[PDB]
Length: 129
Ligand SMILES: [Cl-]
Ligand SMILES: [Cl-]
Ligand code: NA
Ligand code: NA
Image (cartoon, rainbow, N blue to C red):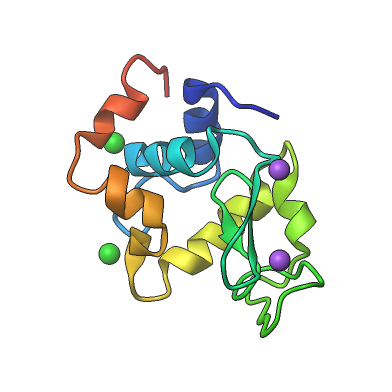
């Protein structure tokens, strides 16, 4: 599923990601835009052999099991394919764990390089939330 911008904002808010660990909703929408273009089905291989999955590009070395990643910890205790669902619940639950890990949203490279320090409220401008 390719979410619309405000559509994803509303889903993320309903799921309690807005202001989660102090990250306003625009941060999460901005991160999803650059990580996945709002596409739940997005996957990308990493150099280390792990793969990133879903709207928030959650990694198979630490967070989910994809059955092919050396050193997988599966800390979210989920198959990586569950993170590709049109229902974002599993991605949100796992993102809450990741962002609590100590580095906040710096865990997402695209967030640090493209969202951090910018006017992230722009990402939810116009939406009815
Ligand atoms: Cl915001
Ligand atoms: Cl933080
Ligand atoms: Na894909
Ligand atoms: Na992989």
